[PDB]
Image (spheres, helix red, strand yellow):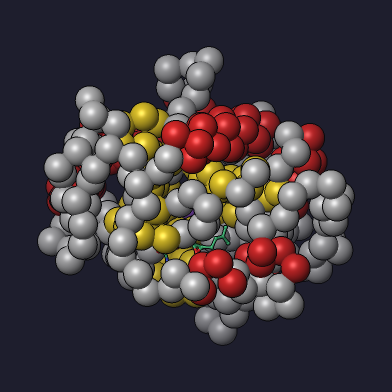
Amino acid sequence: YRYTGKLRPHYPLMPTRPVPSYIQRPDYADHPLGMSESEQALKGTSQIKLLSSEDIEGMRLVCRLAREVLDVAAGMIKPGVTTEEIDHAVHLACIARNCYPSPLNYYNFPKSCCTSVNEVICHGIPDRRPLQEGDIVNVDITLYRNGYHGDLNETFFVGEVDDGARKLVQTTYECLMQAIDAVKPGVRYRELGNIIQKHAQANGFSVVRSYCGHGIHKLLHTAPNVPHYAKNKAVGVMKSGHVFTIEPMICEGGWQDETWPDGWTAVTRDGKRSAQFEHTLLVTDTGCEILTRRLDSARPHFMS
Ligand SMILES: [Co+2]
Ligand SMILES: [Co+2]
Ligand code: NA
């Protein structure tokens, strides 16, 4: 394998962390290949759940808890901390809130969150590498509580970063918020990619194509499929009670991605940096509820 950049995996990984049996587990947790029966049984549909009041409550709860866990991780971002150390703290924080870390054994994914550094686009595997001054790192938190998943991520600065990092991360956040600001009943899912790419391109950045936002609730990913690039073919129309993510991945260079031999880590083919932000959203009649929002600050962590 030829690496696309400077980053390398730092093995071995610490042994898999167990989750006490009293925490309720999603179906894939105990599947030998981490496949999800319940996702399989809805594999290939494009019908979008309209959430019940019970569902809405379940999604508010897990999404609030997911935010608390991201906030734990955010508190640890500094030079010298390894992504495995972050993942360990995330693992314990999920358990402390009676949640299962959704990534863990999802299709045999080995860790309890995704940590994506620099040229990693998404799905980086926490490992023994200490963060370096100048890095950018995304932590993507998914929790499972009482049958529901919630999903968010932020990109963070590790110490002082260069002007390119500041611009990439600011622009990515702007793309997310512009997309969120358009969400409301009657809007086509395919429209969000138009808004995102327009802002990305205006700032000299490209938009990852191979990864999309997604429905989420009792399934970790389901309809709708939500591309972040212009003139996509996404199917469907937003309706009150829809819940899905918007999670744009923006790149300094080209949009092309490839996967490491680990089968998870997605990287820019050119080795240039990529940043991401994600919220889980619930479509309401005036617009949407940002289920994963910060409650105690107006702004994401990187603006500190
Ligand atoms: Co997501
Ligand atoms: Co996510
Ligand atoms: Na990155």
In this orientation, which residue lies closer to the viewer: 93 or 205?
Answer: 93
Residue pictured at 51% horizontal, 67% vertical: 39
Is residue 142 depicted above or below 1 in this figure?
above
Q: Is residue 129 left or right of residue 120?
A: right
Is residue 196 depicted above or below 178 in this figure?
below
Q: Is residue 185 left or right of residue 4?
A: left
In this orientation, which residue lies closer to the viewer: 258 or 294?
Answer: 294
Q: Position of residue 216 (x, y in %)?
A: 45, 51
Residue pictured at 65% horizontal, 43% vertical: 145
Q: Position of residue 159 (x, y in %)?
A: 59, 33
Q: Quadrant of the N terminus?
A: bottom right
Residue 136 can be seen in this image = no
Total numbered circles = 0
In this orientation, which residue lies closer to the viewer: 123 or 275?
Answer: 123
Residue pictured at 49% horizontal, 73% vertical: 41
Q: Position of residue 293 (x, y in %)?
A: 46, 28
Task: Please identify the quarter of the rendering in which residue 7 is found.
Answer: bottom right
Is residue 295 depicted above or below 37 in this figure?
above
Q: Is residue 106 left or right of residue 40?
A: right
Residue pictured at 58% horizontal, 60% vertical: 124
Q: Position of residue 25 (x, y in %)?
A: 72, 55
Residue that extends furthest to the bottom in the rendered view of this protein: 1
Residue 111 can be seen in this image = yes
